């Protein structure tokens, strides 16, 4: 009993469309990955299986590349890990690119695993590769990835008989480029990458009618707007804090298409995103490169230092609605939360609220979680009426974007009940 179906679109390959009208919040599909792996910066910081950042992680005794929070996670991961383990070990000093480790797990899954429910609607076989649109620059990078895969996997895979029938590594990597999902933890931090072939039927819109959220490696696909019968289902492949020009470059470079949506035609929100003096936000955009690199490696004290140099610069400053200033405020907030600097975190967090309202319209999981963070900071600091407003706002959003099937809704409900009990006591 599904409310969605595969169909051949007029000009964007295959897509997913509603078989019946859908309401905001409706669960449309849920999937474990065909294959997934922790990303580089989070390796050794989060559990390889559940992708949570425990304080204590045990590394696998053979390879010592995979780390686990528990015996339970080590066992649930052993089928997925058992053959890559010998490869990671054979290349003891070197570590492969995420894409290479991912495709290794794909190969082992397809060779050794039962048919995956993640492929119910659409299989890895079926995925778009866009090879006839790749630049020769891109094709050259794919060729290098193929040779990297051949090197990394030589201990377990020496020839084609150990690959699925007529499995082509070049085409496989081309598929990974435009069908990889960035797995986010409950705090919306990027922690892993995975393939969800059924979900890969969703085409892109900068104004989508559906949204995905992750609960560990588990993916929930939900409607975030009313959707009519026969209407194509879309998600936004990209970060919302991007101008139309930046979205153009990514959708070209990674997904090989020219976005024609109404937002890109109208340059919707571009002007407000780039307010302030250009030479200032050019420098911030450059600094953000290393800030996000540091954040990807959970380097919070260094993240905070770079952000303070910007937020409290002795030189000219930017409005908080400037998307680069906004990104800096958000990184500083997360840094302060992880360093226990809760007053400072709330200062930065509250500054992001109105910009997030503008740039994450409707029901977007990123805004829901941001508002929940702010409400939780306020609750801990005894600002109950303010916390309650933000916690209910987060619930308004996340009952649509997350739903009862996501464990964070249970946590939010408990915060609401705690905050309400404090307000009632008077
Ligand atoms: C995750 S797949 C989506 C399903 C894909 N259409 C298929 O047939 O398998 C992403 C690819 O679909 C195409 N695509 C996605 N969104 C598009 C859009 N809005 N306009 C044109 N092509 C799009 C691009 O080729 C992109 O690389
Ligand atoms: C049980 C083992 C051989 C396995 N099944 S799927 C995968 N990646 N590994
Ligand atoms: Zn775990
Ligand atoms: Zn291992
Ligand atoms: Zn667009």
Image (spheres, rainbow, N blue to C red):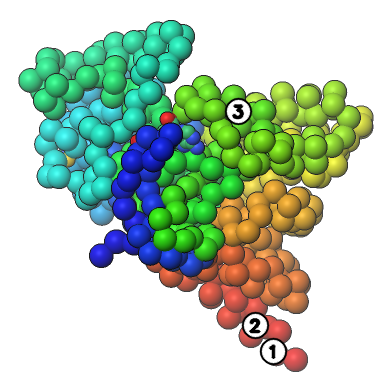
Judge depth for marks 1 and 3 and give the one in front.
Answer: 3
131 in relation to 276, above or below? above
Q: Which of 185 and 269 is in front in this view?
A: 269
Q: Residue at x 39, y 11 (%)?
A: 139
Q: Which residue is drawn at 56% across and 55% down?
A: 365
At mark 3, the secondary structure is: helix
Q: Which residue is drawn at 7% across and 20% down?
A: 161
Name the residue that disc number 1 marks.
Answer: 424
Q: Nearer the viewer, residue 338 or 206?
A: 206
**Position in image of residue 284 (x %, y %):** 77, 29
- Asked if disc 2 and disc 3 are in contact, CB closer than 8 Å, the reply is no
292 with respect to 117 (left or right):
right
**Position in image of residue 402 (x %, y %):** 48, 62
Decide if residue 54 is in sight here: no
Precedes in sequence: disc 2 or disc 3: 3
Disc 2 residue lies near ligand 3 with CB under 8 A: no
Quarter-of-image position of residue 354 = bottom right
403 with respect to 372 (left or right):
left
Q: Could you tell me how far apart the alpha carbons at marks 1 and 2 are, in whole angstroms?
A: 6 Å
Which numbered disc covers residue 420? 2
Name the residue that disc number 3 marks.
Answer: 248
């Amino acid at each position: 009993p599904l409310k969605v179906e595969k169909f051949a679109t007029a000009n964007r390959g295959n897509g997913l469309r509603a078989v019946t009208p859908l309401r905001p919040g409706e669960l449309l599909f849920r999937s474990d990955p065909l294959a997934y792996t922790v990303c580089k910066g989070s390796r050794g910081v989060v559990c390889d299986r559940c992708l949570l950042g425990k304080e204590k992680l045990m590394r696998c005794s053979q390879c010592r590349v995979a780390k686990y929070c528990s015996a339970k996670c080590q066992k649930k991961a052993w089928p997925d890990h058992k053959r890559e383990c010998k490869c990671l070990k054979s290349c003891k000093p070197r570590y492969p690119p995420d894409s290479v480790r991912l495709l290794g797990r794909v190969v082992f899954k397809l060779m050794d695993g039962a048919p995956s429910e993640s492929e119910k609607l659409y299989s890895f076989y079926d995925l778009e590769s866009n090879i006839n649109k790749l630049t020769e620059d891109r094709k050259e990078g794919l060729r290098q990835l193929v040779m990297t895969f051949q090197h990394f996997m030589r201990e377990e895979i020496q020839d084609a008989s150990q690959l699925p029938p007529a499995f082509d590594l070049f085409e496989a990597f081309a598929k990974v480029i435009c069908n990889s999902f960035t797995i986010c933890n409950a705090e919306m931090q990027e922690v892993g990458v995975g393939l969800y072939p059924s979900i890969s039927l969703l085409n892109h819109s900068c104004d989508p009618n559906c949204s995905i959220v992750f609960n560990g490696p588990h993916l929930l696909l939900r409607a975030v707007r009313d959707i009519e019968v026969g209407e194509e289902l879309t998600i936004c492949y990209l970060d919302m804090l991007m101008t139309s020009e930046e979205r153009r470059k990514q959708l070209r470079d990674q997904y090989c298409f020219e976005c024609d949506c109404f937002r890109c035609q109208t340059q919707d929100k571009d002007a407000d995103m780039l307010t302030g003096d250009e030479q200032v936000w050019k420098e911030v955009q450059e600094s953000l490169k290393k800030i996000e690199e540091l954040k990807a490696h959970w380097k919070w004290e260094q993240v905070l230092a770079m952000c303070q140099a910007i937020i409290s610069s002795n030189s000219e400053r930017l409005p908080d609605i400037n998307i680069y200033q906004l990104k800096v405020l958000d990184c500083a907030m997360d840094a302060c939360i992880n360093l226990g600097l809760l007053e400072e975190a709330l200062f930065y967090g509250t500054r992001t609220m109105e910009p997030y309202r503008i740039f994450f319209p409707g029901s977007h999981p990123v805004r829901g979680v941001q508002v929940m963070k702010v409400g939780k900071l306020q609750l801990h600091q005894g600002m109950f009426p303010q916390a309650m407003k933000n916690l209910r706002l987060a619930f308004d959003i996340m009952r649509v974007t997350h739903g009862r099937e996501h464990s964070l809704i249970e946590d939010l409900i408990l915060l609401l009940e705690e905050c309400d009990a404090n307000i009632r006591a008077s």
